[PDB]
Amino acid sequence: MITTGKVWKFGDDISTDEITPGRYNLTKDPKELAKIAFIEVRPDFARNVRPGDVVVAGKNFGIGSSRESAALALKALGIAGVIAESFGRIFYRNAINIGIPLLLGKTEGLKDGDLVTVNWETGEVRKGDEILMFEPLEDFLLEIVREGGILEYIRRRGDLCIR
Amino acid sequence: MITTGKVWKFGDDISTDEITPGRYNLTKDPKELAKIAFIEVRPDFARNVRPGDVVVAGKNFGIGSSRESAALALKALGIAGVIAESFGRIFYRNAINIGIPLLLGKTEGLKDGDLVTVNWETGEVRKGDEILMFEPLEDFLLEIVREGGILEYIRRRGDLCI
Figure 1: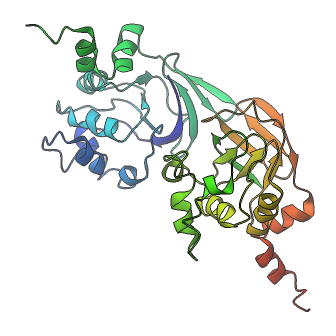
Figure 2: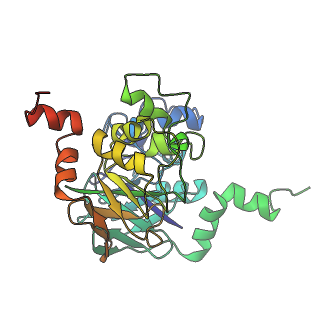
Figure 3: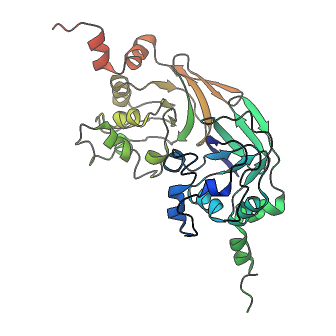
């Protein structure tokens, strides 16, 4: 999976509460959630993000409460995936479950507004004439993302239909 | 004249009618045209294009109707320019007059979604660390484009005497 998009850059310790602050008390509605992703920390994000854009962050991206609405909001917006130095355990989980690709590594070389082409399988990020390498998700996880999330994964496989 | 953006690739014989359907020119608002650019052939283009992006096509880009709306729509969207193997004669003229730079050359090497930095004056297109060369508009034409089209060009360079 290779995508081309704009970098939306964030600092360290972005909490899931900052991803979906006000709307979010659970209204799973992907459409609605898309309207308030990063609504306070980055008011410009929600209305200007386009499919293929990438959320890039520093350390501990997605720490905090276990609200899956954060991952849902990003998915609803067509974000290509998330690149960070490290992720909050719960968010990482929710991103995979929802079907959002993730890359791990130093993000100091990526700035807000940068245009990049990301290969989510190899972790290769092309910026201008340079290439930044990140650790991609292992194959088992890419497979879950490829199917569109863990639920879709087991639905297609048939595990969901127990009887 | 250097821009960086994403390639939106199209094939051969793209008509101006495909760029802006004939049911949309009645407007003195280029922004309105921008909203319907390639609306029927590639619906996500108008909403997803960002200034600096480039339209790349095969041969005969811009044939068909002589209406300027096609070029107007692209410029309104902030499209950096058009790179094609060949252009419809009228579109070429309209592109210049409206104020959009053009590059001529083989485009098989550029794919939809490719990120490119384009030097519209030299024809140098940088894709990653790869360099593709195209034939640019000559300086006189680039000056008209650079100034914003033939009308703005004329306004700034006197000659306002018949």
